[PDB]
Image: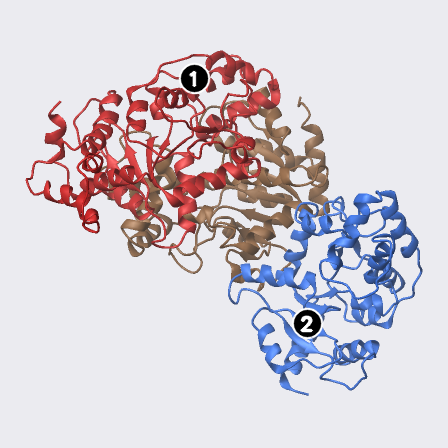
Chain colours: A brown, B red, C blue
Amino acid sequence: LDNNVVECIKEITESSRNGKLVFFVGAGVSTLSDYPQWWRLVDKYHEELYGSPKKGNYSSDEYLRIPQIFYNVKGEMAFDGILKDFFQVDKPTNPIHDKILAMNPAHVITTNYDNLIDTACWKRGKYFSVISAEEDVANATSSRYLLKVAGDFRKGFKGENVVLKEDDYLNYDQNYPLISNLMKTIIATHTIVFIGYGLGDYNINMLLNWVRKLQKDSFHKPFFIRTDPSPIENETLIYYENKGLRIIDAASLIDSNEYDYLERYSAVMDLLIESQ
Amino acid sequence: GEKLKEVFLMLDNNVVECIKEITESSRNGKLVFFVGAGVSTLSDYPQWWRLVDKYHEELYGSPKKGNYSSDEYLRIPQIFYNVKGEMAFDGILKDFFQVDKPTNPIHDKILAMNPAHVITTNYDNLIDTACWKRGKYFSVISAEEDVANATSSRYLLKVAGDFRKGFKGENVVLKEDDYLNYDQNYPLISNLMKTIIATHTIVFIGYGLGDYNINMLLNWVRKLQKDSFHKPFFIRTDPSPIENETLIYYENKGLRIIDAASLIDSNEYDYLERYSAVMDLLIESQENKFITKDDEVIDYIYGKISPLFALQYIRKIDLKHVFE
Amino acid sequence: LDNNVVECIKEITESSRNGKLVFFVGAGVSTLSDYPQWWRLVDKYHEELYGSPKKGNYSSDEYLRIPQIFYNVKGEMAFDGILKDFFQVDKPTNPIHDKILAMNPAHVITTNYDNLIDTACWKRGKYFSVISAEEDVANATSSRYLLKVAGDFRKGFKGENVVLKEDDYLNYDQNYPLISNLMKTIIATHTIVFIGYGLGDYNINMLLNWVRKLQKDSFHKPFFIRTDPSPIENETLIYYENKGLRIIDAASLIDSNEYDYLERYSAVMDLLIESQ
């Protein structure tokens, strides 16, 4: 019924019983809680600086520079008020945030700047530690960790706390030294399962650049959950298998429509859950 | 024809202070052009999207159905190299880049702007043929070994490799492995590029303000301290005019932009009209045709003769060298 | 007893009772156990390198290049045999190893390549996970780590395993990627107390550089135990209270002559043990 992923599940359920499994939760999970996807905000910086909305599919150059262009031109207070008006919203808890916590993970690292996984923790009662700035690594009060590597809005709705702009991705190891370093230790020691990302995200490939610098057979290979609608090519699967990743695709396990994300995330995860 | 003189009177104070400083550096011998893919495509040279249409179809069976995402567009020649080998990667490069295409009139206008060096990200041979037609020799540098074995101290610095040592893919940086190992594989091409920018006047031709080369060069400029470096010039040849908020953002990053859609009115596909309206506006400002003020003829004769007040007498056979 | 040494102890005991105290075992605790110091080894090369022994003193260049020349000229089997001739020893444990385990450390990180802290933990029953090479970072069996950051001779008495040559010290971020990460992850989440270095040791200068990359007040400032004969001057003390090394100086607490090393080490540790 399945091809070569039957060995992939058995290590995960072994990692679930051992308590050595860490999910790398992404925005593909958080977009399921009808949270504002980031392209809506870029349009708000677009339509205030250009004086008109985007007429079509804009260029990838101005996909990382319109958050920065509004930062350098319109200032800091105007950039901060828009982060209030688009992020001070209440979204409910997705089933996936129960399904991710159904496996009882070792740590939860995420690039999500919301509080949605920070809501399903205390609702289910699993006590984690929210580290999102540099002042929380040394004042960490628990061996279990919730690591928000892109910052969050706990200290307020300002631009100083969260990684959005272009400068915050380049000047990143020179700004978050212990959150970059705490992440690479977690990936070294515990088994990483990606969920909620494509095979072309900024945060996914920057890991695979690091994995090649490591020694061969020194790392346990990361798993990837692909929930894209179109199925992966046979040459694309071998390109990330020969770069560290072990892809578990949803488009080859179940048959769904082109807009059926929540049905795709559950079918992989319940296959992981029901084995345990 | 005479449109350029009535363009010139419609320039604002920003572009006039760009043309006065680009042309003062060509006269000093401190002008360097940084040539991109824009002047190569005006000679019909095979663009890199015509290659990435070959790989995705010899690696995925069928031609493309939809637009390339930036995730896919960067990584298709690496999937072809890893899966389908290294002799077939060099075969596709051999199939498309055996052309012997002509040099566009823009290759003539760059060299007629009398440069000291020409840096290029183009792996073509088009700029190197045009330099040898004229009576100046450029030491072509495309590998690591060519820097210490340099000859003439006027470099044609091909920072993206070249196919002079064969049609092999290990001599030209094209893939993504070649984009992240560039500082490791090319330590001396990078240092020689960054020293010319630090010591000369730079004009960028053939780019569009979002490029991997312009962005990795404005990151190096962010590391330099304030007011120690001359700001590079950037010629923009795009159909849409530049918006004012973008020209603020790139002037604070250290680019002095001359928009070509802001100087002339042209069609969306007439790229030689936009390239020649900025290059001819520099070339005809040096070959002094935009002097119709009758007190700009005073500080032109003064700027060439006020040195000669330190001497007592000057021969008249020497004054025909003062005025070139 | 001044308040500064008092305020050093009142944290370290509270870190030991909370299980967040990590000792950094250094070259001091092995020479008290009379393990062969490295300078007689660089003598042994310099008896076959230049052909004649040390008529005078050495230079800091020859302190760092005499091993490398022998491995290049005499070969690879001649270098490993000299390490074989001097390291087939069974030296006993000092009491200073026992004063380190007496505070119940959360981790023990050392740059010593001997098995002396291995045997000191085996006798007292403190089971740890020795990580010396890079195939042990992912294959670790526990969460209490015994991290040899300089390698160990468990695989063999060969020059490949242990960083001794000049090429071995410059390619440390390229031969030990994870251990260079696993060390700094422990420094941020614990209280680090150094034992067994001078102020100008090469391993201490590298840790003082990484703290400069860190932020202001984002880290708990580690503690240094300096056991030199002459007491440190108060001017030198202020220079390390901002670079990131609180100093408990052993010479300013008791009286001892110019060669009683084990007296100076035993004094400062009993102030820690009797406080708990």
**Residue C195 in the image: above or below residue B155:** below
Question: Which label was assigned to residue C224?
Answer: 2
Which residue is farthest left? B294
Q: Which amino acid is tagged 1? A: Arg
Q: Which residue appears at 54% of the width and 34% of the height? A: A265
How far from the left and from the top, in percent, is residue B4?
A: 14, 28
Q: Which residue appears at 50% of the width and 21% of the height? A: B163
How far from the left and from the top, in percent, is residue C9?
A: 68, 78
Q: Which residue appears at 81% of the width and 46% of the height? A: C71
Q: Chain of mark 2?
A: C
Q: Which residue is mark 1?
A: B50
Quadrant position of residue B3:
top left
Q: Is residue C149 at all visible to an observer of this figure?
A: no
How far from the left and from the top, in percent, is residue C160?
A: 80, 45
Question: Which label was assigned to residue B215?
Answer: none
Do badges 1 and 2 share one subunit?
A: no
Q: Secondary structure at mark 2?
A: strand
Of residue C80 and residue A73, the one placed in the foreground of this image is C80
Q: Which amino acid is tagged 2? A: Phe
Q: Chain of mark 1?
A: B
Q: What quarter of the picture does the N terminus of chain C occupy?
A: bottom right
| Spatial separation of the CA atoms under disc 1 and disc 2 | 63 Å
Answer few, some or many: residues within 10 Å of disc 1's Cα (few below 14, many 20 plus, some between 14 and 19): few
Q: Is residue C56 shown left or right of residue B88?
A: right
Answer few, some or many: residues within 10 Å of disc 2's Cα (few below 14, many 20 plus, some between 14 and 19): many
Q: Is residue C49 shown left or right of residue A112?
A: right
